[PDB]
Image (cartoon, rainbow over all chains, first blue to last red; front, side):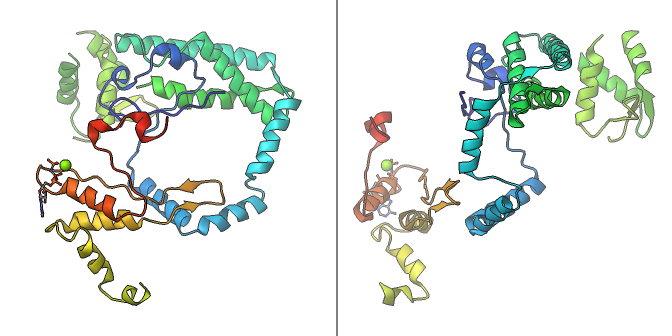
Length: 239
Length: 96
Ligand SMILES: Nc1ncnc2c1ncn2[C@@H]1O[C@H](COP(=O)(O)OP(=O)(O)NP(=O)(O)O)[C@@H](O)[C@H]1O
Ligand SMILES: [Mg+2]
């Protein structure tokens, strides 16, 4: 196993810049990682307060007792016992996928491939973070490892759900990252506090055509619009 | 040492005593004092080790005693090494 740690180009991730400019690594080496995490300082004040209280509890030496209580409570295990347990799992078990797990994984592969295709069209360039058939095998290995914890001789639907969730939380999240006329049209034609049902906006804009969903993503990130009611109602919530 | 440590002004007398022939720059003298005494290095049950050393950057204009401060710290610290700019290679800094 290769566990690697790196900073982006420009050191801090530089969010408004393209990922293809922020990421040094070629798509060849990137594809060899089952999970790519892009880690960012969220700067959220509640989180920062929480981290500050935690880190103070580290430096004060409170954490020495806290970890021991957590271990004796059975909510945590030690370095030594975990080391032996990883060895035992690596020597006892090597699970297969059930047929149901196999189908869910296969359909998930075509789903994420479609997402990458449309994103490459929307950004009109090949993505730096890739999704390839090697990355299906990444989700397969993760599924098997998740079953390998409990020494289950087969992986099951639940393990595939967690494997898919982890891949979505890591490699997809790494991959995930004229309209100016249409947005001011929507601002003109939907005043504050009222709702346009989405499909009518789609018909009107088409009747003038993919600029619609870019406009909605921008206006939803801002306070001006709120996608109420299962996304059916475009609500001019803010300015 | 035990006697002078009792003085209410001892932190300030130490800080004033850092590089005494350099005028002003009490912030630099404070940063140098903090670095030269250092923090406490810590190790959380052996499972997580934490830096005790304090790293300091003197960023600024020419003719403002920065190099002289560093030469003083080379004079004063119990183990010290000094390496200017282009004179330091990657392996000459860490190991080779
Ligand atoms: N506050 C000061 N008190 C006394 N001498 C000073 C002071 N500021 C500068 N000098 C003198 O300025 C000269 C140059 O100091 P030096 O340490 O090389 O400055 P510097 O900050 O390193 N400038 P530079 O090397 O161009 O980045 C020395 O001979 C010092 O004595
Ligand atoms: Mg200098």
